[PDB]
């Protein structure tokens, strides 16, 4: 028997479904999503890191003009300065005094620290959602890990599970992301080979060990100070460091729907968005015929306490007279209230206690214990605590549901006013009928 | 301010705290009509005024 | 200078674009797509291959009934046959004449050939396009390779190229593909863990070296045949082999747009769909000032022969006054006529010869050389060959706006009919004015 159901994607809240196979005792399955993971498939655009400005020792031509040659180095910059009179510690460098020239050259190489301290600019396309699901099957807790794309069959205890396809394709990642250590950022990094100085991606490389390096740091050489041999340069500082000091907040702190963002591999975990179709193929061995299950007659419901505290505040005590000892699956007949217990052992003439959570002002509902139903009505009070640390176990309620004795009141008011309207209609109709008799 | 969907607060390096509001009110849902409308307003302050 | 243009996404057909910088001699660039590759990002769903049935020796118990336990083997099937009287070569094996039992057990495991002969069921999400482009830059013929997703700006000879993004996201691969060796098939393979006997995917595993094998071959043990010691079995044959013998044509032969398909990695080479934006950042040193470029006068055009076929069936001869010796670009002033050559050397008072292709029955176009234009007129004859083995080089077929010469027949007919209508309208207007002018 194949049973198809839909469960909200919220993590940690169990939902119960009634598998009703005619000719067999009803079965109740409680399923809870322990973990839902969206792992996007990443195509690495490039690697950014800190650059290193390599400046070899300057050349000093004592009497004459030096010249340099262009090179294929990533950001090679050369310049010759005339009229330099550099000094070493022992005095003037050489005899010729004003004709001296200084050849100064520099370039940029991606640092060795690029192997460990780097940011990876990726593109993300789609997520292969996977789910860990806890199912209360045959009174035992079983765990199934299955891809949520609707195309993974997981068989446990001869029972087959198909999970997915998830309704909502929303993912916290956009097309282009940046990963650094354990932090994931959603930013539009500049295209490869067109980076800008002083910002993110000024120096770029396809892989951390790649030997090609696109670097744009505006490395401009300046005139050395008089009487010195240093090589000054004006350069936009490493944009990777500026980004690090000004990263902002990562995705795990700003993602919507409470998603938890992780790295290695990049994952989005527990996004409470959309819902999950679940299809369960259950073998015949798990079902019990109605004639073998207990038959319950003369059953009544009482509600000693009810508070809509989102923590199963209501309690129901039901008196039953069972045909014989056994177990039977208790299930609520309405969507407004949810029963914590999935099944109860029953024997003889006794009473059973269940705990339910609701949001109704008056908990009027029906409970299907074995194959019969019993009606419960309750006077439910609001809880005293304002805030709790767990999501509500009860479901959201519609307009007519919460109405309770206010509904009892609007019944009186509407009845009276509509009775006035009906009396007016009768008077108008009889007056019109009399009027047409006078011609 | 904790909205209906819940609020997640990260304080320093501590693990984030999660808060959800529940249906608390100073009125009563089975008393006099003014207490009724007070309860029914306090729980859902937006569309109760619309329906009333 | 930034020049943005659009070229149709075809391979082997060069296109001419005109870079017009005011104050500079016009430049013409010939771009040709050598290879456009669509590489979908594949996530391996699973591996299928030929199964091997392992059958241990049957257990013959003479004077007792054999019993076997359930085993966690992938498709373990075990049975006991009573009343067997097996024979070996030297006579009866079992002394007890009756009541003897044979215990027959067998299971399924993926064979060693799964490391070499296997089919990979993949999921395809989105392709990262790449393009190889040949550019006619400064009289040199250069080649540039770049991703075609509006990214990967690539600099060659100081010229910066930005390729794409593709105008169409069409890809020949469906969501699910199957790769065997070099043939990829658009097949909706069964979901993992839910294979069917005798079809593709009856035995599945996540990766070729995985020990996790899901096998569904409905292996059923049958009774041994009358005194033999064999263990017969009835099993659906390898669905992988049946798929091999029934593969059909792969995507290499059935894909539209003339796409070619390759594997390792999976690529869709040369898909002629949509168009391609190209952005070129030409260095200022590339351009030549108008004063230094030749200025042509006394320029006239004639056509020795024209055949409105592919492969440049038209030839034109143009006479010019070159003024200063030099070279300059040649461009067509209308799209329906395409000139093969891009630049021409002009000197003295010689004449130049150009080759052009068109679908026009009557060539009526203008040619721009060295910033001055000529009007070329020709009557073009239809070709003799019905079919050629190369794509059309002219831009396209004519539209209703462009007929041939001797369209003056249409002008004469329209003029005569409209003149009759106009004189009739004049007579009608005069008569109406007279009628309204009464009284
Ligand atoms: C301290 O700790 C940090 C954090 O872990 C370490 O950083 C890690 O460094 C590793 C070594 O570089 C990184 O691992 C790999 O390095 C490879 C070097 O060549 C690199 O190529 C890898 O990237 C490929 O593989 C990834 C995983 O499969 C893919 O996600 C990625 O996209 C690359 O895959 C290619 O993608 C292109 C896309 O165009 C395809 O065309 C190719 O076909 C793909 N090839 C393959 C084989 O898939 C990868 O980076 C590791 O990533 C990195 N950590 C993180 C979080 O990124 C420091 O090294 C460590 N310190 C020291 C001293 O070790
Ligand atoms: C005879 O010749 C055939 C080919 O003609 C050879 O087949 C090749 O065999 C190789 C080794 O067996 C294959 O190479 C790899 O094998 C890995 C075995 O573990 C396999 O895991 C690899 O697949 C993963 O890695 C790739 C690159 O990193 C990814 O592109 C690929 O998608 C897989 O990546 C993840 O895979 C897991 C699997 O569960 C998925 O869950 C993830 O979602 C995947 N992530 C991503 C991002 O994709 C890889 O296949 C090689 O592929 C194979 N050839 C072909 C065409 O497939 C035989 O070996 C050879 N035999 C002999 C004896 O010579
Ligand atoms: C740009 O690059 C080409 C060479 O590149 C090669 O060809 C490209 C189309 C492309 O595929 C590249 O990947 C590849 O590497 C330079 O020259 C082109 O090719 C030949 C080279 O000799 C030129 O001349 C040709 O020579 C043939 C042999 O003499 C001759 O028969 C051709 O004329 C006739 O050929 C065909 C038969 O195939 C015939 O049917 C026609 O009627 C045609 O007249 C041809 O003249 C080509 O002209 C060049 N290609 C083009 C499209 O013009 C090229 O020089 C280089 N650019 C520069 C500035 O040098
Ligand atoms: C139901 O009735 C309750 C009591 O009548 C309400 O509780 C009161 O709610 C009001 C507003 O909602 C609060 O007023 C605020 O008070 C804070 C400071 O008070 C708090 O901090 C001091 C610090 O010394 C502490 O001593 C107090 O006891 C409070 O804990 C102000 O800063 C605000 O501006 C504002 O005035 C009352 O404080 C609060 N009192 C109590 C005892 O709870 C309750 O809100 C009502 N519920 C509903 C749904 O209406
Ligand atoms: C099947 O599993 C459910 C819940 O799943 C469990 O949750 C984990 C935290 C672990 O406990 C795992 O064993 C398992 O995945 C079980 O229901 C849970 O049972 C526990 C103990 O039986 C309850 O803990 C108690 O909760 C009360 C509530 O007031 C506390 O006061 C106690 O101090 C104690 O912590 C837990 O509340 C309960 N949760 C729910 C949603 O019912 C279930 O018992 C289990 N069944 C079987 C047959 O294994
Ligand atoms: C006439 C007087 C005496 C009583 C009238 C009470 C009415 C106006 C009150 C009763 C409690 C209230 C409802 C209880 C539950 C729901 C469902 C929820 O999803 C939206 C709010 C909504 C729809 C409330 C709106 C206002 C409401 C209908």
Image (cartoon, coloured by chain):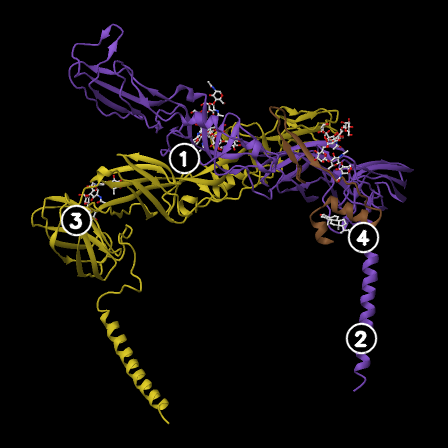
Chain colours: A purple, B brown, C yellow
Q: Position of residue A158 (x, y in %)?
A: 69, 35
Q: Is residue C258 above or below residue C409?
A: above
Of the residues tagged 1 and 4, which is closer to the observer?
4
Q: Kindly check if marks 3 and 1 are in contact, taking CB atoms under 8 A apart as contact.
A: no
For this orientation, the residue located farthest to the bottom is C439
Look at mark 4 in the image and give the residue it sits on. A407
Tell which circle, 1 or 2, labels the residue nearer the N-terminal end.
1
Q: Kindly check if marks 4 and 3 are in contact, taking CB atoms under 8 A apart as contact.
A: no
Q: Nearer the viewer, residue A259 or C430?
A: C430
Look at mark 1 in the image and give the residue it sits on. A190
Q: Position of residue A284 (x, y in %)?
A: 73, 40
| Mark 4 close to ligand 6, CB under 8 Å | yes
Image disc number at residue C370 = 3
Look at mark 2 in the image and give the residue it sits on. A429
Quadrant of the drawing holding the N terminus of chain A? top right
Tell which circle, 1 or 4, labels the residue nearer the N-terminal end.
1
Dot 4 falls on a residue whose secondary structure is helix
Chain letter, disc 1 residue: A
Residue C47 appears anywhere in the view? no
Q: Is residue A6 above or below residue A269?
A: below
Dot 1 falls on a residue whose secondary structure is loop
């Amino acid at each position: 028997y194949e049973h198809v159901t839909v469960i909200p994607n919220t993590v940690g809240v169990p939902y119960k479904t009634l598998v009703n196979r005619p000719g067999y005792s009803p079965m109740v399955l409680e399923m809870e999503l322990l973990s839902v993971t969206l792992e996007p498939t990443l195509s690495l655009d490039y690697i950014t890191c800190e650059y290193k400005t390599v400046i070899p020792s300057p050349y000093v031509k004592c009497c004459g003009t030096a010249e340099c040659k262009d090179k294929n180095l990533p950001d090679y910059s050369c310049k010759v300065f005339t009229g330099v009179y550099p000094f070493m510690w022992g005095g003037a460098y050489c005899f010729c005094d004003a004709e001296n020239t200084q050849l100064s050259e520099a370039h940029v190489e991606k640092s060795e620290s690029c192997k460990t301290e780097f940011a990876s600019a990726y593109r993300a396309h789609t997520a292969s959602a996977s789910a860990k699901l806890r199912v209360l099957y045959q009174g035992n807790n079983i765990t199934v890990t299955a891809y949520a794309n609707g195309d993974h069959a997981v068989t446990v205890k001869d029972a087959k599970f198909i999970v997915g396809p998830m309704s909502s394709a929303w993912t916290p990642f956009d097309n282009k992301i940046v990963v650094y250590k354990g932090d994931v950022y959603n930013m539009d990094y500049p295209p490869f080979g067109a980076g800008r100085p002083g910002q993110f991606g000024d120096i770029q490389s396809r892989t951390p060990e790649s030997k090609d390096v696109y670097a744009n740091t505006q490395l401009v050489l300046q005139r050395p100070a008089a009487g010195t041999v240093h090589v000054p340069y004006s350069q936009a500082p490493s944009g990777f460091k500026y980004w690090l000091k000004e990263r902002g907040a990562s995705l795990q702190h700003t993602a919507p729907f409470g998603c938890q963002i992780a790295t290695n591999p990049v994952r989005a975990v527990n996004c409470a968005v959309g819902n999950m179709p679940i299809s369960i193929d259950i073998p015949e061995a798990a079902f019990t015929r109605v004639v073998d299950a207990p038959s319950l007659t003369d059953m009544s419901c009482e509600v000693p306490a009810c508070t809509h505290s989102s923590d199963f505040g209501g309690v129901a005590v039901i008196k039953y007279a069972a045909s014989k000892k056994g177990k039977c699956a208790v299930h609520s007949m309405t969507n407004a209230v949810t029963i914590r217990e999935a099944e109860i052992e029953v024997e003889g003439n006794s009473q059973l206690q269940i705990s339910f959570s609701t949001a109704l002002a008056s908990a009027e509902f029906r409970v299907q214990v074995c194959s019969t139903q019993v009606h419960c009505a309750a006077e439910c009070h609001p809880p005293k605590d304002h805030i709790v640390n767990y999501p509500a176990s009860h479901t959201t309620l519609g307009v007519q549901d919460i109405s309770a004795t206010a509904m009892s009141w609007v019944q009186k008011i509407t009845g009276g006013v509509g009775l006035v309207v009906a009396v007016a209609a009768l008077i108008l109709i009889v007056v019109l009928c009399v009027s047409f008799s006078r011609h | 301010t904790v909205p209906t969907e819940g609020l997640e607060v990260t304080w320093g390096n501590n693990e984030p705290y999660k808060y959800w509001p529940q249906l608390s009110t100073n009125g009563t849902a089975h008393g006099h009509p003014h207490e009724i409308i007070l309860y029914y307003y306090e729980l859902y302050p937006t569309m109760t005024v619309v329906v009333v």
